[PDB]
Length: 164
Ligand SMILES: [Cl-]
Ligand SMILES: [Cl-]
Ligand SMILES: [K+]
Image (cartoon, rainbow, N blue to C red; front, side, top):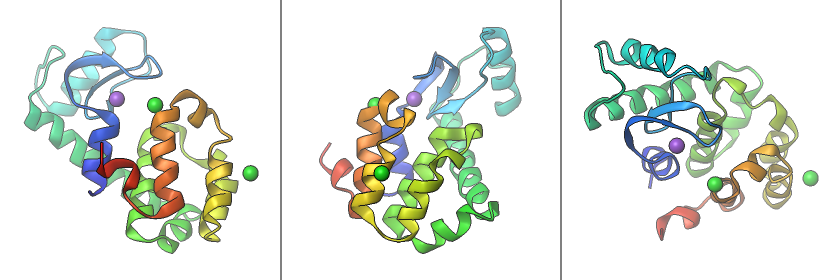
């Protein structure tokens, strides 16, 4: 288990444009295309991302390429965030993966609302942080995924993923 395998489980793999949990056009392994209700706008974003006229369908290799880019950009974004970087740096590798997962899911919305949770994580108050993380729209809207991510933050193990 690593961040790629973890996010692949949480995001799934679809080769045609579909709507995510929030109703937004997405493709591949959790690659959000747009928040616009226009399918044509989503198709245009897809073409831009892939570099060809896709008409809403991609290959597995193309999906994996976007996924590599998206994971990389999530990590780089964390490191460029002056407030978030210290929290990330304080974590072990397994909990770092949980942080990348959350950042990936939140996308452009970001994680500023998680400030109190992130402080508790930095303090290594794992059970307290887990309780605080669940007091969120995130947990309520995607509780199974949030429970997996929270267990990863709480324990620093892959227990919520390894036996699926
Ligand atoms: Cl709390
Ligand atoms: Cl869920
Ligand atoms: K998804």
